[PDB]
Length: 280
Ligand SMILES: CCCCCCCC/C=C/CCCCCCCCOC(=O)[C@H](O)CO
Ligand SMILES: CCCCCCCC/C=C\CCCCCCCCOC(=O)[C@H](O)CO
Ligand SMILES: CCCCCCCC/C=C\CCCCCCCCOC(=O)[C@H](O)CO
Ligand code: DMA
Ligand code: DMA
Ligand SMILES: [Mg+2]
Picture 1 (cartoon, protein in one colour):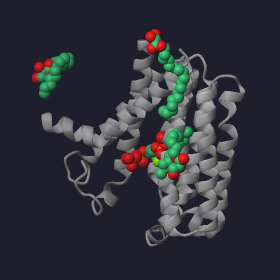
Picture 2 (spheres, helix red, strand yellow):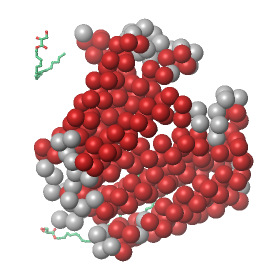
Picture 3 (tube, helix red, strand yellow):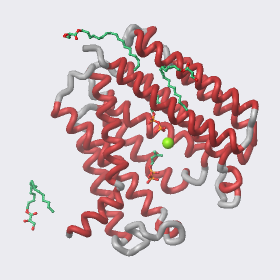
């Protein structure tokens, strides 16, 4: 049972879940202004943990045949865990997450249910269909924060963080798809750069631009101060510059570089929200 527990932790991808759970705490810290309550923290950490665990397991169930070719070392294609054992496990992880979220509030259950439907549908069909998949990737990453946010007293700064993450991650996903265009085409993957070419990069720019318009709101609404405003300013200008370069040079090389830059900037924006939250 020492080896079996290691196999079940490999199936859920325990590192990815803890990463998502920390994201959920981050959101709760901002919302409560670091005035953290241990009982609410334990609910937030584990609801995100089990909803994330369910998603990773449901992903492996629908990918058992695909994984048999690419990376057969995974728990399901290697035969370490039976398909039925995985299906019963994902059901248990799901009930745990949903029942636990009832003890937070109505908003937490709504996010829990919406995440659960998106995770199942993404694993089932929207992983291959990027126009909807790119939205899902954006929404789910942002929802992690919003989940911790709805548990705290001031959700407004976490609402802006969720909206900005969704828009910028969705945009960056189309940018990644423009770089992976040649590979995706010879795999039966439908994406905006495959259907529209360079035109899609204007929609990726639009999503980044809309995120930039919403970014000074915690300052304007008198929630966050000067350090947020300065960190956001550098990042907003760098975002508009990054997309401007890609629109001027719409190639695989530039798309690859802009994709790396946007990930760094997104991490500084997260730091700016944490820094802004330190109001004590
Ligand atoms: C990351 C790069 C950006 C550069 C950082 C810019 C931040 C500037 C912040 C200004 C506020 C000053 C806080 C320091 C108070 C310490 C002296 C207070 O005196 C003391 O040490 C007392 O004994 C404490 O009780
Ligand atoms: C591989 C080393 C890991 C050891 C973990 C350290 C434990 C420290 C804290 C308490 C353990 C959790 C509570 C016990 C749950 C089930 C006990 C019921 O007992 C058992 O699980 C059976 O005795 C197993 O045969
Ligand atoms: C590859 C992506 C990495 C970029 C991320 C930028 C982080 C933005 C946050 C603020 C940095 C604080 C400024 C202090 C550095 C000194 C300026 C020295 O800098 C300058 O004046 C010239 O830029 C030097 O060439
Ligand atoms: C960030 C994101 C899009 C979450 C979906 O989880 P997944 O099951 O697709 O993730 P992974 O491929 O890491 O198992
Ligand atoms: C404001 C903002 C975009 C938040 C941070 O996102 P992240 O660090 O989770 O981004 P990713 O992991 O998708 O690069
Ligand atoms: Mg991502």
